[PDB]
Amino acid sequence: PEERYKMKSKPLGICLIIDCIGNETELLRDTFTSLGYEVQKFLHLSMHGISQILGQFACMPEHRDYDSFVCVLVSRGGSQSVYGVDQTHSGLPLHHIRRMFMGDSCPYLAGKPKMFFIQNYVVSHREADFFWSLCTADMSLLEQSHSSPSLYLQCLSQKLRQERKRPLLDLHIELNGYMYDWNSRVSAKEKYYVWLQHTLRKKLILSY
Amino acid sequence: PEERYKMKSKPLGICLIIDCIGNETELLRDTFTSLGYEVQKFLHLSMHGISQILGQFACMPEHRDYDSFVCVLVSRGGSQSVYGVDQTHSGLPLHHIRRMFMGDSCPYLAGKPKMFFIQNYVVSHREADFFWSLCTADMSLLEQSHSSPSLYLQCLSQKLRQERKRPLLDLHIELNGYMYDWNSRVSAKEKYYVWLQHTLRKKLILSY
């Protein structure tokens, strides 16, 4: 009875990683490579560079042969937007990003789980099958150490790599609990806020 | 290892039902009574009546002895607000509702799952442990038949009553799929849009 997203293709799908800060530390490259994804990572992209690359990945016909898609984005930004490496106050809207992968603009992934994991650093029907995890943290953390991976990326890597058989949603609940516990022990500026929004229609497990 | 919210008290908690339309049809009263909740239902409340009652339920000291809280609200409203039976265009903000049950204003439910299931009809740290399911539907459905329960309430009742051992989140995923399938077969005005937002930190199952 219980429906589950088909997850059998080899690779499971493409995992697009855009790290505009430099602290992703291969954590998710290694994690998703280990889960069976084909990872392509890019560094030092401006907003225009981000759109160029996102546009190209949304158009690949090889998605047709894959069961899912993963996108990891690490960037400075505002609420609901990313700046890439640009010094700006009007960033690339996040909704414009997910918009590029909706069924109409991206037929090849129609009916397939499209997962977005975003680490943002800020200054203090066609929409079914999307998984959108957004972590916001204070920009001061980058001034202190821009090469140190956020706890969100570390925890995400740990959970997916160590418990790939549990549903993604259940792992994310534990990540929620993990971030809440961290937040309760540190100063305001060291905290991580995690927002999750999804339109999944079936149980999603990143493995066979 | 896997954490799960404590669910053993008798009753599991209070289930507050506010039906300002008249179509709840005892579906959730029966469902939650069957799961072990003490149900209290109110009808024909204005925005002021809704706040009066919500305020009283947020203050009950008996929550101290319960493991959770459930609130079902059925009302005409705007986006993110409910009018109760008032003819108005500025309703009671939904965020003002959840605000009344946060840890600071509601210590007795601190660390406990607070579940809100809302059916709205519209014209075309302190925040951990909240589960917020909001269904929006077109007001024209009430003109046609204000006593007919929405499919959202019917499906919710069916899932919880027939599969009380599965986590609430997994049931809600199936409800998502159920609503998407319904939406794909009918006209715009008969559709139901479901928005889910939560801050759960552990697996939530409404039974022992």
Image (cartoon, coloured by chain):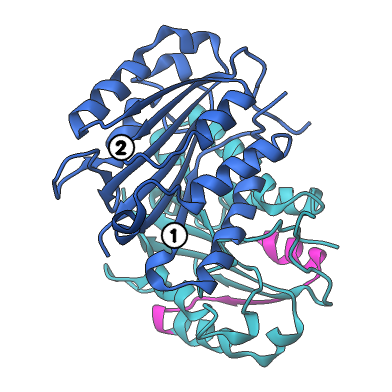
Chain colours: A blue, B cyan
**Residue B59 drawn above or below residue A107:** below
Which residue is nearer to you in this view: A146 or B1?
Answer: A146
Name the residue tied to disc 1.
Answer: A193
Disc 2 element: loop
Instruction: Give me the chain letter of mark 2.
Output: A
Label 1 amino acid? Tyr
Which residue is nearer to you in this view: A18 or B160?
Answer: A18
Judge whether residue A134 can be spotted in this image: yes
**Residue A26 drawn above or below residue B78:** above
Across and down, in percent, residue A115 comes to: 49, 33
In magenta, the rendered stretch is B25-48
Which residue is nearer to you in this view: A48 or B80?
Answer: A48
Circle on res. A96? none
Q: Identify the residue at image location x=30%, y=37%.
A: A20
Question: Residue B6 falls in which quadrant of the image?
Answer: bottom right
User: Left or right of A26: which side holds B3?
Assistant: right
- The reply to whether the magenta stretch includes residue B29 is yes
Question: Residue A178 falls in which quadrant of the image?
Answer: bottom right
Q: CA distance from mark 2 to mark 1?
A: 20 Å
Disc 1 element: strand
- The local crowd at label 1, few if under 14, some if 14 to 19, many if 20 or more residues have their Cα within 10 Å, is some
